[PDB]
Length: 20
Image (cartoon, rainbow, N blue to C red; front, side, top):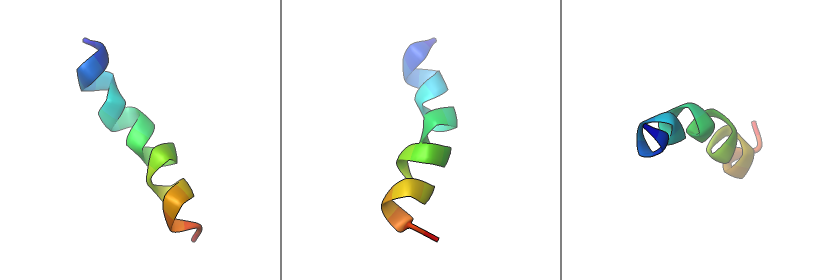
């Protein structure tokens, strides 16, 4: 269930690493 929630974290783990 966590590994599936990561996707939700990508919104921060991504957008963050994207800085934009």
